[PDB]
Length: 136
Image (cartoon, rainbow, N blue to C red; front, top):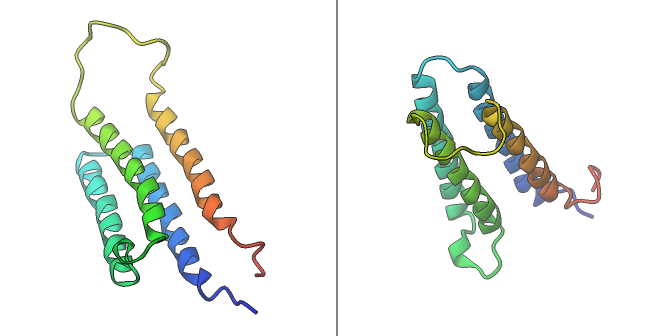
């Protein structure tokens, strides 16, 4: 007889997770001023750091053999880096180049927008598929 007691944590962790992503999409959709982009990256960063401390005291990855907090940490790490790449790519401009890529017509932005929500739908659902159903 389980009432998703322990699952209440992981579930409450996905709520904000998916929300954070949208935040990055809302900004990219509303390109206004520069302070919005600067505060955005700094904001998303705080969310991650805050999460660390959370589990830090609640059974951290450095106090077990097969921790779960570390799992999401890995996938999140590689994801965070990807964001930094785009952040800088926009900050600085590239005046002409020696070579020319193949394809693309100014949709590079829209590409990262979908490529993100996609990898997220799989990841979020991946851990959400743990339970047999909503009525465990």
